Image: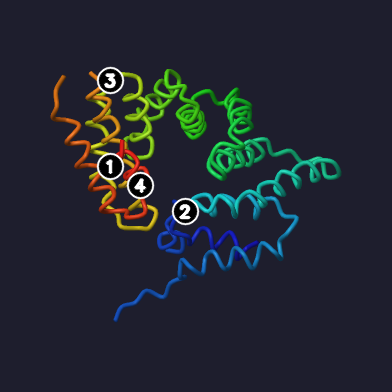
């Protein structure tokens, strides 16, 4: 457990200052790819430990490896319910976090399947916090999925007001705004949302393409309401999308539309 917690404290995701904490010029350091391996090796030795599970789940979720998180969370909750029965220990905040994590996994894992449960869960924990962003963004995405924009917008605005740092929310909001009928703001929001990414990561490119495609869709929604021009702009954005991703069907579909 020591090794696990220290490993996390040393981790890049972690908000702690490892240099200050202990206070060709290659720093005698712990490799990030070693953090995870430490976690994995040592949690197997710490199995039946609550904290280790929590922390591992957090790490895996922070890296968008949701599929890996689900079992560690599921098991994690089991510990809490088992640990309370004999020891009589209570850790409410932890349980609430775990459940939250489960909700997110249910939100992303397979697209629409476990959303309905995620919602019940989000509400279940939201009842306490009310202000919570991570949950409202969840509900947001769920509602964006369910073509239920009137709520998606209102939630997404409130979570966006907390963090213009995050582009996912800004894009999802812009989308929720476009579908609502404030198309210009959406179109503009996406434009920031495209440049702001500035990544070539495998997970970044398709997202650039995604927003590129979204902008186009909205650009057609602009054509919904005599001008012949903007559709042509949509065509350009799509062409870009197809050009960048090369495996991006919706680009070809829309460009086909």
Taking the spot 41% from the left edge, 60% from the top edge, the residue there is 20
* Front tag of 2 and 3: 3
**Which of the numbered marks, if any, corresponds to residue 14?**
2
Taking the spot 55% from the left edge, 26% from the top edge, the residue there is 129
- Closer to the chain start, of discs 4 and 2, is 2
Q: Is residue 75 left or right of residue 23?
A: right
Residue that label 3 marks = 182
**What's the CA distance linking mark 4 and mark 1?**
8 Å
- How far across and how far down the image is residue 23, in percent? 42, 63
**What's the CA distance linking mark 4 and mark 2?**
25 Å
- Closer to the chain start, of discs 3 and 1, is 3
Residue that label 4 marks = 207
Q: Which residue occupies the extreme front position in the image?
A: 256
- Closer to the chain start, of discs 4 and 3, is 3
**Which of the numbered marks, if any, corresponds to residue 212?**
1
Taking the spot 44% from the left edge, 51% from the top edge, the residue there is 15
Taking the spot 46% from the left edge, 25% from the top edge, the residue there is 147
């Amino acid at each position: 457990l020591a090794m696990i917690l220290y490993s996390w404290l040393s981790s890049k995701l972690s908000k702690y200052d490892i240099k200050s904490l202990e206070s060709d010029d290659i720093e005698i350091g712990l490799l990030e790819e070693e953090v995870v391996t430490v976690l994995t090796e040592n949690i197997v030795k710490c199995k039946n430990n609550i904290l280790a599970h929590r922390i591992l789940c957090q790490y895996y979720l922070l890296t968008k490896e949701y599929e890996a998180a689900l079992p560690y969370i599921k098991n994690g909750i089991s510990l809490i319910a088992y640990n309370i029965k004999d020891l009589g220990v209570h850790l409410p905040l932890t349980k609430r976090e775990f459940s939250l994590d489960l909700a997110t996994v249910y939100t992303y894992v397979d697209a629409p399947k476990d959303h309905n449960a995620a919602l019940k869960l989000y509400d279940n924990i939201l009842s306490g916090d009310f202000s919570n962003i991570q949950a409202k963004m969840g509900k947001g995405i769920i509602f964006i999925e369910r073509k239920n924009w009137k709520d998606a917008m209102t939630l997404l605005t409130q979570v966006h007001e907390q963090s213009p740092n995050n582009l996912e929310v800004l894009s999802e909001l812009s989308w929720s705004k476009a579908h609502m009928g404030y198309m210009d703001e959406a179109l503009a929001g996406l434009d920031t949302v495209i440049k702001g990414i500035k990544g070539m990561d495998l997970r970044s490119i398709d997202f650039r393409a995604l927003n590129l495609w979204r902008q186009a869709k909205v650009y057609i929604m602009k054509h919904a309401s005599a001008k012949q021009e903007n559709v042509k702009c949509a065509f350009k954005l799509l062409i870009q999308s197809i050009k960048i991703l090369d495996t991006f069907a919706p680009g070809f579909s829309t460009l086909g539309d």
